Amino acid sequence: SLMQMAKTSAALAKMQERGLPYISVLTDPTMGGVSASFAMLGDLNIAEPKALIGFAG
Amino acid sequence: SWIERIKSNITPTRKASIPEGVWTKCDSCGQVLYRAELERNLEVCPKCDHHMRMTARNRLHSLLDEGSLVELGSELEPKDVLKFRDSKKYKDRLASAQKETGEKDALVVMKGTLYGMPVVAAAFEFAFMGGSMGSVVGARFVRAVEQALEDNCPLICFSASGGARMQEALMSLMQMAKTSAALAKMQERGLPYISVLTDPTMGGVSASFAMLGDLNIAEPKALIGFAGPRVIEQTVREKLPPGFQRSEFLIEKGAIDMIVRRPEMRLKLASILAKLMNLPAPNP
Amino acid sequence: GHIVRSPMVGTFYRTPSPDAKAFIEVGQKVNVGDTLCIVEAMKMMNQIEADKSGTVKAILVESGQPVEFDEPLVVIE
Amino acid sequence: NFLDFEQPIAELEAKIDSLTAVSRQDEKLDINIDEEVHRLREKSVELTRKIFADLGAWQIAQLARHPQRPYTLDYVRLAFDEFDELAGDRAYADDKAIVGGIARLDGRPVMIIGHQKGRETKEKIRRNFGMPAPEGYRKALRLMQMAERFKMPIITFIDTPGAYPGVGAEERGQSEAIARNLREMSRLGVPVVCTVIGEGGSGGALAIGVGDKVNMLQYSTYSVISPEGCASILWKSADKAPLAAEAMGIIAPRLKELKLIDSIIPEPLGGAHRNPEAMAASLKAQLLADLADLDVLSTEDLKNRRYQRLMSYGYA
Amino acid sequence: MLDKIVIANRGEIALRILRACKELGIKTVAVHSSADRDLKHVLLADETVCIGPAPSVKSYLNIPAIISAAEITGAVAIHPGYGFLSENANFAEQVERSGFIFIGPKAETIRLMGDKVSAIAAMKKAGVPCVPGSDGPLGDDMDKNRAIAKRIGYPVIIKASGGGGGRGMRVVRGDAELAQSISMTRAEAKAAFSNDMVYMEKYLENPRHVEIQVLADGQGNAIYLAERDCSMQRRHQKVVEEAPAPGITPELRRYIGERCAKACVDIGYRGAGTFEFLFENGEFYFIEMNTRIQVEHPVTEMITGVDLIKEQLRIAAGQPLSIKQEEVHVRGHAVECRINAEDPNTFLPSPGKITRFHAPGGFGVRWESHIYAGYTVPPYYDSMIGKLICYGENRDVAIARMKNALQELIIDGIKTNVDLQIRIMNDENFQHGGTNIHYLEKKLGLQEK
Ligand SMILES: CC(=O)SCCNC(=O)CCNC(=O)[C@H](O)C(C)(C)COP(=O)(O)OP(=O)(O)OC[C@H]1O[C@@H](n2cnc3c(N)ncnc32)[C@H](O)[C@@H]1OP(=O)(O)O
Ligand SMILES: Nc1ncnc2c1ncn2[C@@H]1O[C@H](COP(=O)(O)OP(=O)(O)O)[C@@H](O)[C@H]1O
Ligand SMILES: *C(=O)CCCC[C@@H]1SC[C@@H]2NC(=O)N[C@@H]21
Ligand SMILES: [Mg+2]
Ligand SMILES: [Zn+2]
């Protein structure tokens, strides 16, 4: 699973360099690997109210 | 009985003459110094190791090898148009500084070589109206960057200024963008640009190209920042932290790469540039 | 009281320049921060600042008279 | 300070120390030191094999945390020269839990990024137990970009308990910084090699570990979560950490078969700590070999291969 | 002649220089520290200047304060003596340039010969034999270091080229600790003398310390006076020094003296200085040059009849040598015995007050010091409080007088190294004369049960 973060990051880079936007909307819970992989990486980071977002529980 | 003497006083009439320019002082510690010793230890008080001012031409000579020096932008001179009427006339200060320091403006540029490797250097003569970044300063900066771009060779500079040249008003401010554009044009090429900060590095110069090079080498106990300590003191109306805007503090706060003392500087630049340019290591 | 003493060796001058008013003179008291004399050494005319605010009772030296380390200069009562 | 299972090795060492004193201590005492030294060293060498033959994954983790070991500073000193440490993120601080710099490897210039737990208590607390706040990872990104720009290879060491779980670390975009790191490193035009010296893992380690090659010592654990954490969440306890270590597959050979790491660098007997110089030499040889067969490929082919290898991640 | 000079030193050498100055009619200026207010030479001097507080660095090494004194009093030269600022080439440069005359060699030779390795190199170039060794400062090429060690032959010794006072030297038994020993020796040199230069030189196990005194005016004249021998040492620090040395036939005397004179001419040496050596099996291996006036200068004065300090003060006044090589004669034999404030065994300084004191006197006995009753030894500098001598027409007579003088001598209030001097004098081998430098170190013995 851990390695998948890099795969997702590489794909997102491949797309951002193209010009296609990638908006990631965070919803509780957004924590640990997912938060630090592509949750926080898109052009925009839209957090729905009162949602729990971070890295460490 | 000599064991018990009178403790006589000295006779004032006795008089010996020492040459005037052979003994200097270090106000940082108070130890009188032998001028030739201080000048041979790159203007570094060997007692308290407190760095002091150095002449721009002396600095360039110190770094560059001997006999390869080539000054750049020597025909550029101030051409005040704002006729700024201060308590003095801006032309008055311009001429006074030019004659007192022997340099047209704060910045001097001298193409040269480092351990057989071509390089371009420059520095600020802080004595020149606080070493402000005048129009000529930015123009010479552009000239040096252009020289570096045309001839593949790292470009180096040293920072010493109290802020942009007020008397030229917005003309100086705009130069920051010119310098930034030139530095971008060079960084995109692959030619490193190392800027070594020296006290004082403040105001426009600090925020223009002092902090912009690949590396940011702050000489110890140097004052680096953006807003002068008096301005911040009046604004926050409080006590600034100890070591404020000090290289030993701005390496703690991430803005400053590495603290290098002046004697190593030439080797430190030579080794780092010979690495980055991917050239064989220099021979001591 | 207290005696302030030269911390270095050199010629003793009270007027900063050949024809100048003395930094201090008997009578007028000084404060902690003020220059009291000039101790020339190698043409670098240094200066001496008191540490205890009080009256200048007297001056134990005279201009042109060399002084040594810890040489008493002025006594403050 | 040897571990609990390295006791027989210890007491034999404890007899060995006072041999120096007995050489010139007092009362004319200068005994035939050489004979006793040779016999006791023979016994100690024989016994360590009797001790390090039967260690498994829970131990491996203990050895990976031996409080006497080479950190990135040690490997830099013992395999690298002309080392220049760049400290500073340019934003808010330089971090002591990460040390980076530019050095030479057999003439060749390289970039070195890795963690440094500090040796004793003082340098451990000054470096936050090798736990980097995000500013550290921003610094690592900055250095990696610099290395990419000047056609320079990157050598990275990875020895971190994990990204710091603290207020200051979370406030400053920990997740954001690590995401960016994982994004940029996957586009550099320069080869990347990354070891797993010491104890590493927990994602934050991956911030500087996405490269063409990956290598790991024989006693280095690379776990998405520390065994104790997995034990607490799943086993509902802490004492059952060894079971978690056995299940997860945190040991190098277990990972090796998983196509996750490209090579294991064998250690000196009893752990690399007994012969740090030998470990440094082995690491330097492995790094040079990795770089060699890597420089043949061009930058475009390098990046394409890197991307392809990433996609191989996961059985899917 | 020099119209006035400053005694930039303290004590035995200070008082001795003061006597020489008053003899030659050259007024004197005593630069003292605040603790050394009531020294003998201070009280017997024309004009006394205080330059700093008790510590050496604040007061006596305060080159600025010394030059201040020299300028205010109107001197036209300065005598540093030995110790404090004896070999500080930079002090020589500053004194030269400030406008005064540095009594001694020109700073250039101070720099060339204060670096031991450059000194040995120039000596090799000038024909003076040298000890096998690195032949250069040690680098970080451990392979080359061990190759040289194998070439010269173990054991070996590490010596800091900028070290002084018999400190900063370590003996290396093998390559096992060669790197660590070198590192710690360099660290000690950096800490003490601020200089890191270290070099490798062969180790000799049976040396007989020799040193030949030379006077050169710096104008192409260089002469060599009698020999010396400081064989007896404790921690490489001399205690007893006999001049000339037993068994040095006049052939060897003149042979080495001519080479040393040629060396002084080549270096263009100015002032009084001494080429140390090391002796065994009829060979000489240069090891250093003390480009100053040594401590055991008397033991050449009483056998040659020439006052060295007066020769120095004449050279500094520009006068060439007034003594030819032939006209110099060694008539007899001498011996010297330093007195120091240490514990006779522990070798811990024991500064204090001297309640009672009584010079030896008597024929042939010379007492150099400043001590006297009521003189509280300052616990702030070297531990020497007198250089006692006993000149005889042969070694037996000179030792005899020494024994008698030491019997007479009383110094009370502070422990001192008189017992040890008596015991050395009574030693059979020493009375024979010709022991190796270690002799005293070996007598020390070792552990007992
Ligand atoms: C907004 C700007 O960019 S310019 C604003 C001025 N600068 C700042 O606010 C930043 C720092 N402020 C300062 O006062 C200094 O630079 C400090 C804090 C480093 C102090 O350094 P100091 O040793 O006090 O130097 P100082 O300010 O006296 O500079 C020396 C001379 O340069 C002059 N000077 C310095 N900067 C400038 C400037 N930007 N424009 C005009 N003159 C200047 C000063 O007027 C002074 O002249 P003077 O001695 O003949 O009166
Ligand atoms: N190469 C050597 N071999 C043996 N002994 C030596 C050697 N060099 C120095 N020594 C010992 O140390 C003493 C002092 O050496 P020297 O170089 O004069 O040092 P210092 O500058 O401390 O007086 C010598 O008299 C000798 O006894
Ligand atoms: C240099 O000529 C040495 C003598 C010191 C001259 C200076 S001028 C300033 C002081 N005033 C004075 O009378 N002498 C001192
Ligand atoms: Mg010696
Ligand atoms: Zn200073």
Image (tube, helix red, strand yellow):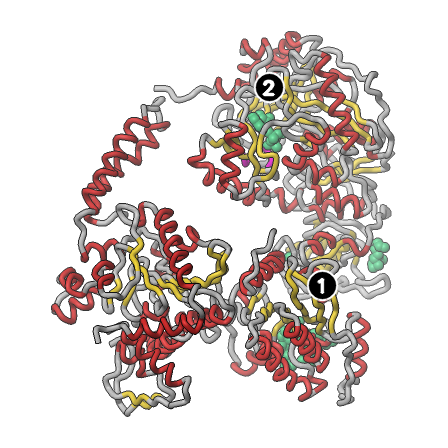
Asked whether D312 or E136 is in front, the reply is D312
Relative to B32, C11 lies left or right: right
CB of mark 1 near ligand 3 (< 8 Å): no
- Label 2 is found on which chain of the structure? E
- Establish if D265 lies above or below D269: below
Asked whether D133 or A14 is in front, the reply is A14
Q: Which residue is mark 1?
A: C35
Displayed quadrant of residue D253:
bottom left
Circle 1: is it few (<14), some (14-19), or many (20+) Cα within 10 Å? some
Mark 1 element type: strand
- Establish if D299 lies above or below E72: below
Relative to A34, D93 lies left or right: right
Circle 2: is it few (<14), some (14-19), or many (20+) Cα within 10 Å? many
- Label 1 is found on which chain of the structure? C
Most extreme residue toward the bottom, as rendered? A49
Give the residues drawn in magenta, as a range.
E163-169
CB of mark 2 near ligand 2 (< 8 Å): no
Mark 2: which amino acid? Arg
Displayed quadrant of residue E114:
top right
Could one spot residue D37 in this view of the protein?
yes
Residue shown at the point (25%, 65%) measured from the top left: D259
Say whether residue D160 is magenta. no
Mark 1: which amino acid? Thr
Q: Nearer the viewer, mark 2 or mark 1?
A: 2
Residue B68, x across and y down, in percent: 73, 61
Asked whether E402 or E110 is in front, the reply is E110
Asked whether E230 or E259 is in front, the reply is E259
Q: Which residue is mark 2?
A: E208
Residue C35, x across and y down, in percent: 71, 63
Relative to D97, B195 lies left or right: right
- Establish if E283 lies above or below D77: above
Displayed quadrant of residue D114:
bottom left
